[PDB]
Image (cartoon, coloured by chain):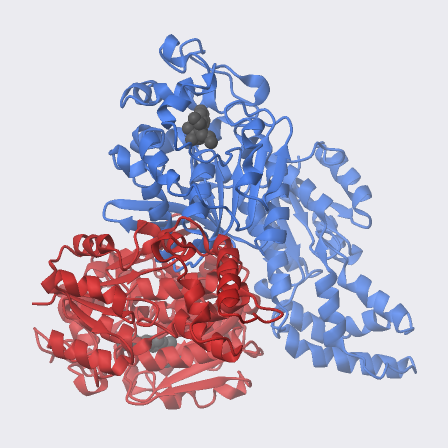
Chain colours: A red, B blue
Amino acid sequence: TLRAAVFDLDGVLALPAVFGVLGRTEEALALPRGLLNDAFQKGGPEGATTRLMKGEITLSQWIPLMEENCRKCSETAKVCLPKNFSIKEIFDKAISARKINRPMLQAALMLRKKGFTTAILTNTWLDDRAERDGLAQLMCELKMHFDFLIESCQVGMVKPEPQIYKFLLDTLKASPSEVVFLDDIGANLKPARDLGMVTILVQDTDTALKELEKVTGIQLLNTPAPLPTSCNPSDMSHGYVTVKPRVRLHFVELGSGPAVCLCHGFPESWYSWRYQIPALAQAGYRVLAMDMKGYGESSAPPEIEEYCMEVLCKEMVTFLDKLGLSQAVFIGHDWGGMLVWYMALFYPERVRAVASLNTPFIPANPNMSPLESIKANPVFDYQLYFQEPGVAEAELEQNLSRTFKSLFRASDESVLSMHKVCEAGGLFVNSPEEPSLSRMVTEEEIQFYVQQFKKSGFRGPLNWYRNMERNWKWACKSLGRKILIPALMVTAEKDFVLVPQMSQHMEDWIPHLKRGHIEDCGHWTQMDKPTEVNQILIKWLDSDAR
Amino acid sequence: TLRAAVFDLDGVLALPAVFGVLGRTEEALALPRGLLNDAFQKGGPEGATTRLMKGEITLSQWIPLMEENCRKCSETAKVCLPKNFSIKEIFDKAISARKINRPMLQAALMLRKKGFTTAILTNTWLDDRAERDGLAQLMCELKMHFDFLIESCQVGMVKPEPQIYKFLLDTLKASPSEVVFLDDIGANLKPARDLGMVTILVQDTDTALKELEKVTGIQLLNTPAPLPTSCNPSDMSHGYVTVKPRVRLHFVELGSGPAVCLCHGFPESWYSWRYQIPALAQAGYRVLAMDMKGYGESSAPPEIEEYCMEVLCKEMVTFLDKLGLSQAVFIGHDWGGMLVWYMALFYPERVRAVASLNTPFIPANPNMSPLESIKANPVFDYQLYFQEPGVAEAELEQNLSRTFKSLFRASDESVLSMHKVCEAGGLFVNSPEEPSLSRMVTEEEIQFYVQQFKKSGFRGPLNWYRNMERNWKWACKSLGRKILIPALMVTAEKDFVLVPQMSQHMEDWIPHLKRGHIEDCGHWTQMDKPTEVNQILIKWLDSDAR
Ligand SMILES: CCCN(CCC)S(=O)(=O)c1ccc2[nH]c(-c3ccccc3)nc2c1
Ligand SMILES: CCCN(CCC)S(=O)(=O)c1ccc2[nH]c(-c3ccccc3)nc2c1
């Protein structure tokens, strides 16, 4: 019974293959068929390419050797190489043209998710070309999805030498009959077959996947659309900044490029951005996903005023200063969405662009207290419940698993009513003791939140609702301003607290506002519709945030 | 007696001033003298500029108001504004031209170092122009050197209103007679004078500094060249990556731009890069200063093999992968210099550029064991002392303060002999028990190292010398390679272990090698000659690392 799947890079996980471009170059230059491919393989195990694949020489040291082989080959064929024939040029664009074979990676990912140990086995070189980064970026994206990456230039062995196959079985901790091996080269497939491995000769991906699905018994073809890549907490880089004595801010960091600060809502974690962090980093951004003040590994002082918008904003400015960042794109959801609008209002020079998910920007009414206007809308009764220090903490901290299982639900899964929470005497009053596990979350994801909330509980998180009057007074000072920096508002159709209609007057204050909208999406936008969230944010970042 | 110094931004800390460009624009366009300045101040406390300075409106909302004031002014003067008169354009280049007044910041820094509480008090706006980053970068660089930054648009008060002066005294916790106030505008100086503050009317910086030096009694003019900005450990962002189970890597991070990985030597810390971290970040790089394996807050497994070059290099590759970094510039010193050459030799696709301080690149002799070649040079006897597990740890860990005080010394300060350490039976045998404090380090800097080394001691650090044979065998596989990626070698004249002559044959293997050289510099390059190290690295990074 198969338990490991081994994939080649060139012609299997990466398309098009180099020897396919070697053939396309022969045709384009009207050279004899196989001339360039014969030059490439010249001297077999004793030649220039074998030395390169074993790591004896780098790619640059190899170029003039491939040049001489092409001259010597063209001399025997009694042909002429063109005026400006260049191996450096041919190989540069061949490497550059090569992209990930998306259906093949998806099947590799399906196999791994279903218990298989996966590996990439490749005949590759030490790339020291000035353009090496393109390949380095390609390898980084592929390697993260596999248990092993075996490169010929790193092990000093090559395919089809039987030693690399014996090396592969040892790293896999599997006997041959337990391994599926996918290769585009028949000669490199033969030693795996000889040992007793299941082998697939890759030509077109569809035929190879049909063969792979039949042999594994796992459906790889015609599968439902997969969720975006998520985060494993212990595989992330964890950052920590002291913004003031006894107040420390925790963040997860991934990627290079413009700084993208992600600000979660109530009662969440940096982990709420799990499906955005890899996608946004892959899109060419340096993601800094916050544990907001009061949450996770960040400091949770007990005083209410410590959570007023003026203090939180000033602290995010200090966070930027301490990391040596003149600007960041601020993307917020829920309470994070609110903070993000205030960062744009009060510190526009530190805000590259601003994006909110569900949270609209509504100017303060100077002729009315916010505490008396909360009462005007029946949906916001839970806000009044959240007011008295102690009450909601006791209910929310009682059974942590029940809290997140009850809250983290889709549009068609509600167990709790948003209205008359005060009259009922709680948020979980006519709610089950053991709520069913929502479709959006696994048991593992709920437990990550459970463990996070054991450190400081709900006092710090609840204090964000406890600065209404203080927040109002500060917001009133911004009444003559306009948001003129690039801004995005993302509405969610089925969010019944942060309703899309609440965002309708936004253009009066943000005239150049760009919009996004998600249908059949509840309040927990990021985990409800991660593929949609990623498309909207990436499209907006590349057009408006550089 | 003065204890606080308050500085204005425009015309004091930042040159040239805006109203100087307003006058230069009048001349260039042949407009009546003061026309643009009269337009700017139109309506005094009830006008457009006062609203902008108080933060009622943003800069962009202000542009069309300044436009109307210019039209109305030009109408009364009975003149015509040019065909393509634009306030946006005038202000854009005025803000852009404005740089830090370096002698003024240096004096502000001298004052702070000598006990003064320093502050910037400025009449400024909320900048929401598409070009706002230039100013945001200017403010970031200045603000870090002061105890306070008071901005009119943030406090809702302006100079010359006496409330801002009363606000300044409160934040300073000082009475007027304790404060020096430097301003280029006489009108904004008058309320500080009225309260009883020492005031300096800034015109030319030299005259103002002569006045400031006379009144404080502190020498600010004709001072010796200051050391570059250093790091306060608790003001840094601290990053943490798990590279494998039970092996975690700690780093300090500052700045945005290309990733610059700094690799310290034996027996050091990320803190050895203290004078490079701010300079390199200011130069437009994202600095990642490592605590190498075995050191500080990074993991120190006890096994020798865990510190072999193959393992350390593989772990730095994992460090890059986990942070989502396809490449980094690798800058190493001492043992870090060695690692850095091996990263370029084994993973050139992950190495943007490579730089070594003191450590040359010498290829492995395949016809000789390194353990028998260490004996060929008398300087490397301490290496033989470092071999037996336990011996050197006991001596180095005995008195931590004595260890760093004895080791961290300049060329003209040696207390320990590099030769016959085995015969003497130790590194500190004929060395003082209470060594004098070297010129390169303060008591505080030595104690940071003392506290760092209390966690794991010297086992992990010493194990880097305990993989000679293992390292040799791995290095032998690279014997046919060449370093063809951008590379820098920095030699130090008075380093008597890593002598500049040891680097002479390097071009045979690194043909495009760029060089650096530091005269009257010992082994501890970074702290011995920080200004020189910074100049060499920044010049090389901007030409070769982008
Ligand atoms: C009274 C107006 C309501 N909000 C203003 C929206 C412009 S609010 O600032 O009080 C606010 C903001 C974020 C919120 N998030 C939630 C929330 C409630 C239950 C579960 C999760 C989030 N309630 C919120 C209220
Ligand atoms: C035998 C050759 C010596 N070195 C090779 C230089 C190409 S080494 O790799 O053993 C080496 C490397 C870094 C070192 N650093 C020190 C050192 C000694 C005392 C104090 C601080 C550093 N000794 C070192 C030896």
Q: From what the image shows, is residue B385 above or below residue A122? A: above
- Classify residue B137 as left or right of residue A341: right
Instruction: Examine the image and state in which quarter residue B265 appears.
Output: top left
**Res. A117 in view:** no
- Classify residue B300 as left or right of residue B193: left
Q: From what the image shows, is residue B123 above or below residue B462? A: below
Q: From what the image shows, is residue A320 above or below residue A507? A: above
How many callouts does the rendering have? Answer: 0
Q: Position of residue A10 (x, y in %)?
A: 35, 68
Question: Where's the N terminus of chain A, which quadrant?
Answer: bottom left
Pick the front one: A45 or B480: A45
Residue lying at 45% horizontally and 52% vertically, measured from the top left: A58
Q: Position of residue B409 (x, y in %)?
A: 52, 23
Q: From what the image shows, is residue B155 above or below residue B206? A: below
**Res. A173 in view:** yes
Ligand 1, seen in the image, is in the quarter at bottom left
Pick the front one: B334 or A135: A135
Residue lying at 86% horizontally and 73% vertically, measured from the top left: B35
Q: Position of residue A134 (x, y in %)?
A: 46, 65
- Classify residue A143 as left or right of residue B438: left
Pick the front one: A177 or B178: A177
Pick the front one: B192 or A174: A174
Instruction: Examine the image and state in which quarter residue B465 appears.
Output: top left
Q: Position of residue A200 (x, y in %)?
A: 21, 73
